[PDB]
Amino acid sequence: KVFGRCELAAAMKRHGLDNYRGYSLGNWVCAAKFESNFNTQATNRNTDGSTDYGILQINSRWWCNDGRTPGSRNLCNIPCSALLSSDITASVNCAKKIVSDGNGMNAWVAWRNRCKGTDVQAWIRGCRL
Ligand SMILES: [Cl-]
Ligand SMILES: [Cl-]
Ligand SMILES: [Cl-]
Ligand SMILES: [Cl-]
Ligand SMILES: [Cl-]
Ligand SMILES: [Cl-]
Ligand SMILES: [Cl-]
Ligand SMILES: [Cl-]
Ligand code: NA
């Protein structure tokens, strides 16, 4: 599923991501924009052999099981395929664990490089939330 901007904002808010760990909704929408262009089915292979899955490009090195990432963990206790669903629940629940891991949203390199410090409220501007 490819979400609309406000549609995704609303779904993220519904699932309790707005201001989660102090990160406003715009931060989450911005991260999703640059990780996946709002496409839940996005996948990308990393140089280390791990794969990133879903709207927030959650990595199989630590967070989900895909059966083909040697020496990895599955700290969200989910198959990586669950992160590709039209229903963002699994991605949101896992993102909550990731953002709580110590480095906040810096866990998402694209958030650090493209969202951090910017006017992230632009991402939810105009949305009925
Ligand atoms: Cl957009
Ligand atoms: Cl915001
Ligand atoms: Cl594996
Ligand atoms: Cl394969
Ligand atoms: Cl594990
Ligand atoms: Cl599994
Ligand atoms: Cl949803
Ligand atoms: Cl933080
Ligand atoms: Na894994």
Image: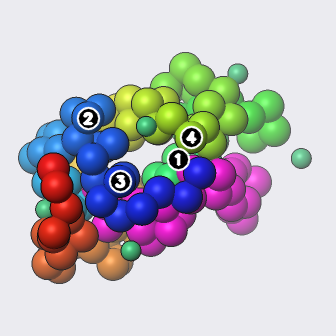
Q: Quadrant of residue 108?
A: bottom left
What residue does disc 1 label?
Answer: 58
Nearer the observer, disc 1 or disc 2?
2
Q: Please name the residue that numbered disc 4 is placed on.
A: 86
Measured as percent of width and height from the top left, residue 77 is found at 55, 20
Question: Residue 34 in magenta?
Answer: yes
Confirm if mark 4 falls within 8 A of ligand 7: yes
| Secondary element type, mark 3 | helix
Q: Earlier in the sequence, mark 4 or mark 3?
A: 3
Circle nearer the N terminus (1, 2): 2
Q: Are marks 2 and 4 in contact (CB under 8 Å)?
A: no
Q: Which mark is residue 7?
A: 3
Residue behind mark 2: 14
Secondary-structure class at tag 2 = helix
Amino acid type, label 3: Glu
Residue 10 left/right relative to 33 = left
Instruction: Give the amino acid type for the residue marked by disc 2 in the picture.
Output: Arg
| Number of residues whose C-alpha sits closer than 10 Å to that of mark 2, classed few (under 14), some (14–19) or many (20 or more) | few
